[PDB]
Image (cartoon, rainbow over all chains, first blue to last red; front, top):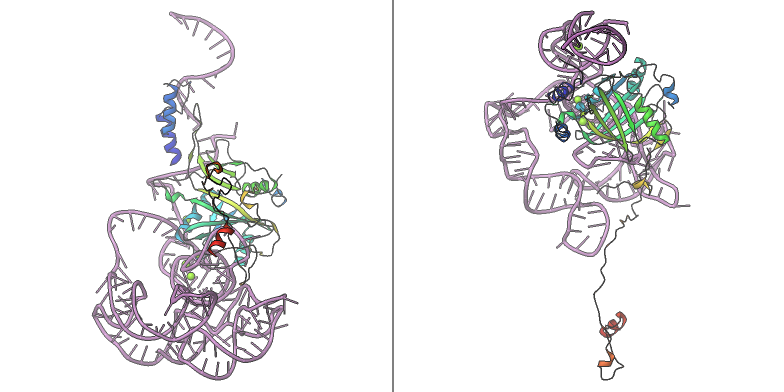
Length: 36
Length: 219
Length: 57
RNA sequence: GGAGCCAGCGAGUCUAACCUUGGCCGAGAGGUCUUGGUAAUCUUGUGAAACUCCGUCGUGCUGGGGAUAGAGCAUUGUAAUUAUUGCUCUUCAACGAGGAAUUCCUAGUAAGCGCAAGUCAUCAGCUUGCGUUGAUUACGUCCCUGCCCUUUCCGUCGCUAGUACC
Ligand SMILES: [Mg+2]
Ligand SMILES: [Mg+2]
Ligand SMILES: [Mg+2]
Ligand SMILES: [Mg+2]
């Protein structure tokens, strides 16, 4: 539903996940946010 | 502090709610009842065809229900929302403005019905705290910390904006998506008793013809 | 139109709506130029409303 | 068209003219003379409607439909030939069950039928309440969809401490 769509969109843009798991301009990231 | 009527069961007994409508509801009002059921986790929608207020309240009180929600409309436009708390009140009446149903959104999807987080803002006056206490106790207690659903009541000039959002915790920020509905609810009357008892004392009422009504604040 | 009132009204009563209408200042300028006149003491400009009404009866 | 015919929630006049029975006049609308009620007392058994019985009509856009329009008879103000709300006659349209799609609904429920009050939000053939007739189907399933609960079960990289390696 909405949550599934929201999580998928964030994952596509790399918003969710880890910084430490092992298997961009900040303005550009802001553009990615606004689109979401 | 929690009100005396709710203090006995505050955080002890999970609220039991019945959502209903006036006689001969329109399709939109019947729709509008549906998300109000979905809004409150422990709500049950009941078809009111020919039910009588003494009969309705008496039957509800027997079943052990906590609160009763009744909806009124005007040409399929939701207009009023009255919440009555058993066994002896209080009864709070509201007017719905700029009502926006989820049926108005295409490809909307399904809701999540976890115990939602609650947000009450700009409630400072004593009457405001009473409104928080009444609304606060419709929902289940102890929402899960990772519960993904948040309901917000924002007080802006006596008009309580109601929204429903689902979030996600990202690395640099949290992004919320509203699920709907949107509606602004204004308290205009409050009684110390069940909705059936028309003679119950009025704790508070909205004076609209006083000269300062145009600029007056209450919540 | 339909109207609501704090208390019931009687048929004989009269309801009124208060409202405000803008007004403008008249751009009239008539300097006194007595020295330019022969008599220098009978300069006459716009007459008073009473005087005008009396003249026209 | 006649006849039979049964509810409930309420409202209603003092320094006034509200609900109005009954009598008379009027085709009707309405007018007129009285009368009870500040009301579990009078309006009021609110003799509501739908509904039942007996009759006319008869598959014909017909005695279904009443949109639009004309002419009159009255009420309300107000002084206009101004509107206003009712009744009489005439006129008599689209509509023959409705595509793609779509919304809601499990017992006094869906649905039909009327009566009452407009009592600080909203509402004016609209809101609320009241009452009357009253069903078909399901009341089982996680198969599809969606939402949850439990593993105080199994994997990947983590973070803390240590050992070495390039
Ligand atoms: Mg119905
Ligand atoms: Mg209605
Ligand atoms: Mg009806
Ligand atoms: Mg079931």
